[PDB]
Amino acid sequence: AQYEDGKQYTTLEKPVAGAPQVLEFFSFFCPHCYQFEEVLHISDNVKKKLPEGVKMTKYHVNFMGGDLGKDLTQAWAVAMALGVEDKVTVPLFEGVQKTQTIRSASDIRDVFINAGIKGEEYDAAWNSFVVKSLVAQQEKAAADVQLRGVPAMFVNGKYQLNPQGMDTSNMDVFVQQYADTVKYLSEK
Image (cartoon, rainbow, N blue to C red; front, side):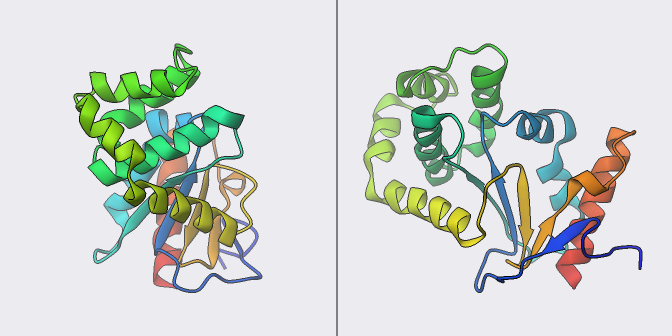
């Protein structure tokens, strides 16, 4: 074939019932995630090629950056709850990996404040049980697929993207190949 198990994707031996259709895992400590978001715009290009009636989910993971890693997962829960993912993703990535001005929960908070979310509104979210379950979901989804690395994408809880098996000579070509694979896996 032209798409073959083990080449552009791998198949999960232990399939995951009821999973989100397109599920992506990242970490703000993850250098390739930085690339995936800021240089490649993977999530967005995948979306551009998905059929619609297709829900796209992105979750943070705990296993990088120790204590701040967890904070970052709670903060992403807050971002999801407030629907401000698009206003913090870039300053969070740059704060962790470019300028290195994120060192504590408080610095994470500053990004939101400067992105216009109100202090009160952030702290309330931060402490809300809706946010707790949202953190729980993120962890549960990671746990369901035996996740030990990011960036990672899963399609219908049964296929995992395999980007090491795609040409990286041209960044645009890498993205299209990636996205087209998601779409093929989507229709499978």
